[PDB]
Amino acid sequence: KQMNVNSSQDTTFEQRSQEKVQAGEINESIEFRNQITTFVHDNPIITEQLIGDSPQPSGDVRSVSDARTHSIIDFLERPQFIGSFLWNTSDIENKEIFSLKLPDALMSPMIREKLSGFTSFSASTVFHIQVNAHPFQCGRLVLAAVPVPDILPLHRLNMLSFDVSNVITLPHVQLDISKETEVLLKIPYVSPFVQYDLVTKFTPWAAFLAHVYAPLNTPSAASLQVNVFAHFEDIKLGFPTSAIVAQ
Amino acid sequence: KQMNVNSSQDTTFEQRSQEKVQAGEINESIEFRNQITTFVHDNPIITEQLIGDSPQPSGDVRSVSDARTHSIIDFLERPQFIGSFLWNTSDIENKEIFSLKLPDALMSPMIREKLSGFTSFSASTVFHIQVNAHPFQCGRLVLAAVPVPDILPLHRLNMLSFDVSNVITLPHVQLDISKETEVLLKIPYVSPFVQYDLVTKFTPWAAFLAHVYAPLNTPSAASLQVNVFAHFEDIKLGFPTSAIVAQ
Amino acid sequence: KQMNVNSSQDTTFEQRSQEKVQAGEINESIEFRNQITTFVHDNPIITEQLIGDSPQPSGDVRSVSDARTHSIIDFLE
Amino acid sequence: VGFASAGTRDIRSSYVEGKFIPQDITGMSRNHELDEQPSQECIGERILSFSELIKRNSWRYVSDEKSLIYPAYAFDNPAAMYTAADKLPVWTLTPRSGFPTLLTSIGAMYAFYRGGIRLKIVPGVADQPKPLVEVALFTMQDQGYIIKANDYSTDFCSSNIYENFVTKGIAEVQTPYYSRVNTSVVSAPVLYNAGNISPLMPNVMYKITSNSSNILLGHSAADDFRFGFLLGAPLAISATALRDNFTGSSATVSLPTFSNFYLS
Amino acid sequence: VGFASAGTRDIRSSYVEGKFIPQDITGMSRNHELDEQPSQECIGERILSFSELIKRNSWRYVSDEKSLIYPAYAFDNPAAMYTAADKLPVWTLTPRSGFPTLLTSIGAMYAFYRGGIRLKIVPGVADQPKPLVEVALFTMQDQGYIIKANDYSTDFCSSNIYENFVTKGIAEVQTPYYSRVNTSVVSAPVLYNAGNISPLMPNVMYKITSNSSNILLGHSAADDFRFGFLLGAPLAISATALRDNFTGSSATVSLPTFSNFYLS
């Protein structure tokens, strides 16, 4: 079967090989699978093609196909520009530049289209914070990660908003705008749920936050854009389902 | 770089290895690729993770992940119930049960979501026509395929609607409702375009049609549903693009 | 250097090989001589020519050049 | 290794993992190299992990019910209020599941946990005629994961342990993890609707019954317990300052300790 | 190889010589690696050099003289004028030696050339009684290197070729380089005083004679011809736009093509 059949089984005599069935029925039938659907036929079938059938030769598509290939995992691993946040001279120590939930912040139409059809997924996540200050500007940011933000005790979330000291104890990386151009933090998937529920959205596994560690310091008022790029890694997909990836 | 970097290159001394550049600039910088995005950094960067970082262990997800894996190609290969068409005793020789364009008829939200992000694709196609008549009913259908339907000369399309004899000369398979339960026809991708244009939709590469070959013959008026299942095979994808998969 | 350079020296790391200088400056620069002039460059330079550059072939000038050569000494003699 | 650098070098993970090694101000690493003599001569032990400390039991809550439903895996700590206003008590604590213990105080630094716990019970009265205490695994799906007097009279065939306040004096229990997941959330939120089926904590509570009018409950980690994902210092106040009375009102804060419990 | 650099890296000669190799935006060089299938399946040939194109003949000039002196190695192109003013023809072309051909159009991109050329002649009339055409090498030192009706009646013993418009139909000639130098100048300037002795072009012209009242002349490179020292795009206009007539005046520009020539 050149019908790219995943498996095929003529079941005509199957009833004749059951131990507790005697003189079993001989019933012309065949079962075959194509990906997630199995066809169980209860009579003969005919499988036809073009005379001398040959699939389209691979060389024909070089004019348009990418030499690189792209699967669902590949799409989820693509860097995405997640946002551009304002940082200015008036922001003081610990001012929040941004706080982005995971996955949430990466659930663009590109990612949603590819996750559609799965119950869930889990992944490590890499965040880049980029700042382009000119040489006469100084300042410092902290990019940190906190787990299961929507179910963490309030005292903990408050501590993060009260004092940057509680952000520095978290897994984090620091950005000195006069020395580094970009800084990255990779966080593995950690949660009571083995994968993130795309159907009920019950519970984002982490949040990445960026707070001012030392204010943007310039001779006159100024502001800079703090940009975020992110992508998933160590991706694990769920199970095929008709459930909608919730908005 | 455990940042699942596809490639990485410290370019600090790159300018020192150009033949026509003398005393080239030593410039701390690094370039790395993640899937389809390349980051070209013009200064030092810091890459941080959890202390003793370990990605989520695979065994943790067995409770939800499918032992089978699913990529874009896998999704496009999934059988789909394309339609249920009426066939009744009053239909005479050559009456058209259906005519479905390719891809068009298979462009369900599931397929569109997975093709989104590609300029185009090409594939062989397998069609199943299924009919469930009871033993006291007889009749016969023809499932045939015709290429580039929207650009074929009108005389040809008319010939198909005028006489079933012009359907029988085409690549086709016949269904005897009293003998076979289902019948399949596989057609390779053939077209002046090396892949189907998802952006401009310019030109469906084929159409599958089912015509009455011998009328449904029963003692009193009756009707049967003629069902269609289809899926793609020998799939070839296009190039990454932001162009919209046209409605 | 096909720039008929009499001598050439990349001096980028020169300050790093002075005995009484510690942690010397790494400074992209190059020095080269052409006859009685020495160019001391304090940054990168680019040296370009025709694609597949080839100087005029000697045979081309036989119609006018003297098989004998003439230098300053020759003229004074 | 070098005292200074142009750009960040002291990175959180690199230092803890031993990849970044700061130099001693004296230049001799021997000055901050471990010396075992002090602990061996002066202390008599050497603690290396909070894993050891949480295995020590501490008092959590005082009950005035003879039969009680208690939220075993709830690790929340009290709400606190402060004031320096005249004639008002300086500090006030309002518990939900109980007061802080080594288990919940160390736990407040982390996001997750897994493993079992242990329970200890001191009786207010060891009643000779009715000396038994029963601690039963409580699993009704309907019950909220909160403290409540027992009103159930239909929880047959439960897992029960019996201890005797007269022949022994203190009840000792070990609770299995019995979780639907492998990673639980420290002080997960408990809700009205919730009941006892949330995946964020083992779906198991205690039903404690005795003839003592009051009991003092305490706990600790079992041998397979662990906290994971360090967050940092939890919101906290000075324990010693709870004796403050500078407003003119006498301090009224009182933690559940054996002496507070046993004597009135 | 690296997408960016601090300082110039993409240098004109380095790229053409293959020393500088830019990276594909996709990171896979295979995406811009030569594929021979397209030309083999769709075209049937694969052109690699303008050397091939200039060997194809194209029409250069129409003469209304029966005997003509023609500037063989003059590769100049017409002067052009444009206007969008009402009722005036949009484009006008004024030739000197002729209109553009593959030879002169490709040549306009270079400064120099060397080698011979070929001449093709189509007759306006193939006169049966006097069917011959003579193409003679013309070398009078006095003649200006320009088009002129033949007034000479004393140019004996010239190099002559004869072709027959009736038995064959098109005259075909090959002209040797016959140059005083090894490098000629494309469209060198021709002057009043000049004559036919300048070293910038072969000192040779054509004297064409037949009994046809009109002839159409065309040319191409001979097998030993070459252009050298690429300069860039020459001053040029859109050929298709020559049909413009938006000013209300009908287009009057007409290039020398067989159809224009043969029919009126």
Image (cartoon, coloured by chain):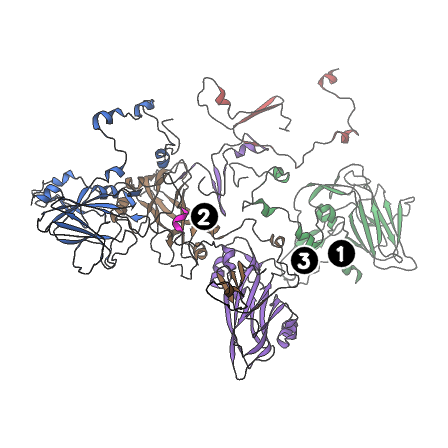
Chain colours: A brown, B purple, C red, D blue, E green
Q: Secondary structure at mark 1?
A: loop
Please report the bounds of the magenta region as a residue range. B55-62
At label 1, counting other C-alpha atoms closer than 10 Å, the crowd grade (few under 14, some 14-19, many 20 or more) is some
Question: Which quadrant would residue D227 be assigned to in this image?
Answer: top left
Q: Does residue A99 appear in the picture of this structure?
A: no
CA distance for labels 3 and 1: 14 Å
Residue under label 2, please give it: A79
**From the image, which quarter does the N terminus of chain A lie in?**
bottom right
Q: Is residue B24 magenta?
A: no
User: Horizontal placement of B32 versus E124: left or right?
Assistant: left
Between D38 and A141, the one lying in front of the other is D38
Residue closest to the far bottom? B220
Residue under label 3, please give it: E242
Q: Which amino acid does the dot numbered 1 rest on? A: Pro
The answer to the question of whether label 1 and label 2 lie on touching residues, with beta carbons closer than 8 A, is no
User: Horizontal placement of C12 versus A58: left or right?
Assistant: left
Report whether mark 3 lies on the same chain as mark 2.
no
User: Horizontal placement of A134 versus D144: left or right?
Assistant: right
Between A127 and D256, the one lying in front of the other is D256
Indicate which disc residue B125 carries.
none
Between E215 and E12, the one lying in front of the other is E12
Indicate which disc residue E256 carries.
1
Q: Which amino acid does the dot numbered 3 rest on? A: Leu
Q: Earlier in the sequence, mark 3 or mark 1?
A: 3
User: Horizontal placement of E247 versus A234: left or right?
Assistant: right
At label 2, counting other C-alpha atoms closer than 10 Å, the crowd grade (few under 14, some 14-19, many 20 or more) is many
- Is the residue A32 above or below the residue B31 in the image? below
